[PDB]
Image (cartoon, coloured by chain):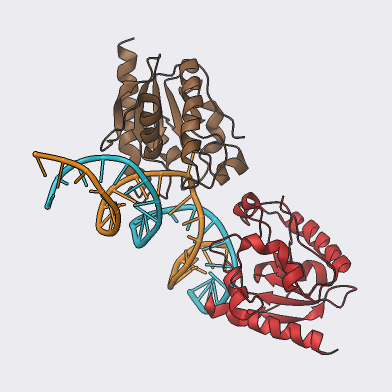
Chain colours: A brown, B red, C cyan, D orange
Amino acid sequence: TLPDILTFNLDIVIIGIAPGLMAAYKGHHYPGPGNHFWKCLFMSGLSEVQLNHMDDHTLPGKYGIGFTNMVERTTPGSKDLSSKEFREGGRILVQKLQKYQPRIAVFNGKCIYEIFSKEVFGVKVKNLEFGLQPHKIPDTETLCYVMPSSSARCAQFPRAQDKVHYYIKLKDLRDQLKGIE
Amino acid sequence: TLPDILTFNLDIVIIGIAPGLMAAYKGHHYPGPGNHFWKCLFMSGLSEVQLNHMDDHTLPGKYGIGFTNMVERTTPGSKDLSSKEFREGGRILVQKLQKYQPRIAVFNGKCIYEIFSKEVFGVKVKNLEFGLQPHKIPDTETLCYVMPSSSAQDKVHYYIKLKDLRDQLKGIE
DNA sequence: CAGCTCTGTACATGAGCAGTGGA
DNA sequence: CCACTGCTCACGTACAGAGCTGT
C-alpha cells in the first residue's frame, strides 16, 4: 500500500503511525510540508542538504535511515485507527525489526510507543518521556527512541524547530553507538 | 478516481473542480466536514433534513441533484492540474451535460467557470459575478450558474436563489 | 484529596486555497 | 503578478472532566 523503505545494517529506522492521505497519493514518505520531518533531518545534520520526500529511497544506503510504519494501511489519520488495529500492527512491526536489526528504532509519535510497550513489553509506562526507552527490541540489539510526531497537527510543538532537539539527540545516540562497535 | 452521480431528468448538477483526496478516500462527494455544501443545502431547503456525505447517492432520486467535477482524476489541490487537462476535462464535461441534460449546471467556485468560459465559449469574462450566466450549455437548454466555492450562512443566499430559479424553470409548465 | 482506566475535547504554527482589491 | 483577510487540514498530543477504591 505504502511500501516500507527498509534494508539491513541501518543506523536508524523511522516508524510512523499510519500513512496519511497525501503520503499515499504521492507514494513517498513524509511529503507534507507541513511535515517537519525533512526539515528536521537537515537541521539536525542527519542530512547535510534539504531533502523533500522524493529523496526518500536514497536514505538507506547513503544516510543509514529507513522508513516503516506501525500501521501499513492508509488513514487520514490518526484518530481513526482501531485499538485492535494498532496492536495487530505491533506484531508485524517487530518482525521486521528483528529481521532487519537497525541500531535504533525511532518511533514517530508518542501514541505508537505507548501501545508497543503495552503489547510488546507488557509495560504500561507511566508518564512517558521522549527519547531513549529502557527496553531493547526483543531478540535484537535495536534500541527504541520516542519522538513527537512530526505532524503540524501536534500543537504542543508548533514548529519544526521545536522538534529538532530530538533529532539531534538521536544523531548523538547514533554516534555513540558507533563508538562501542 | 471518484465516480460522478449523474441521472437523466435532473434539476441540478453540481460541478466541482476535481475531487480532493479525502473525497476519494471516503468515496463520497464533499465529505468535508469543512466543505459547507451539506449545511448550505439544508438551510436553503433544497434538503428537508441535514444530510451528510453518505447520502450523495440518494440525491438525484430523492432530491433531484447530481454531481460531477470538471476534471475527473483525484487531486490534492489545484496546483497539480495543468492547463491542458482542464481543456481536456472541460471538453468531457460538456459531453456529460449534453447527454444527461439537467436543467441547471451549477459551478462551484468562480475559478472553474472562468476556465470553462474562455475554453468552451470563447468569451473571457470581465468581472465575473455569481448567479446566472447568460449562456446555455451547447446544444442543450441547460443553464449555467455560479456559486461561491463551497469550501456558510453568509452564502446560503446563492443556494436559495438557485432553488428559486429551479422552481421557475419547472414552474413555467 | 490523592490513586488509576476510560472518553472525549481546544489546542499551537503553517501551507494551501478562494475571493477582492490592490501597488 | 503578489499581498492581503480568514479559514481549512495536518501520519497528535496534552489537558480537565467523569466515573470508583482505598489508608
Residue A169, position in %: x, y?
30, 30
A74 vs B73: above or below? above
Q: Residue at x 58, y 71 (%)?
A: B50
Q: Residue at x 84, y 72 (%)?
A: B9
Locate residue D17: give its quadrant.
bottom left
Question: Would residue B127 appear left or right of A132 to someone viewing this image?
Answer: right
Q: Is residue A120 visible?
A: yes
Q: Is residue B114 visible?
A: no
Question: Would residue B158 appear left or right of A97 to someone viewing this image?
Answer: right
Q: Residue furthest bottom?
A: B172
Question: Would residue D15 appear left or right of B66 to someone viewing this image?
Answer: left
Work out whether residue A151 or residue B52 is closer to the camera in this orientation and state it. Answer: B52
Locate residue B12: give its quadrant.
bottom right
Residue B114, position in %: x, y?
71, 70
Question: Would residue D15 appear left or right of A151 to someone viewing this image?
Answer: left
Q: Residue at x 31, y 32 (%)?
A: A124
Residue B74, position in %: x, y?
68, 51
* Quadrant location of the C terminus of chain A in the rendered image: top left
B64 vs A143: above or below? below
* Quadrant location of the N terminus of chain A in the rendered image: top right
Q: Residue furthest top?
A: A181
C1 vs A111: above or below? below
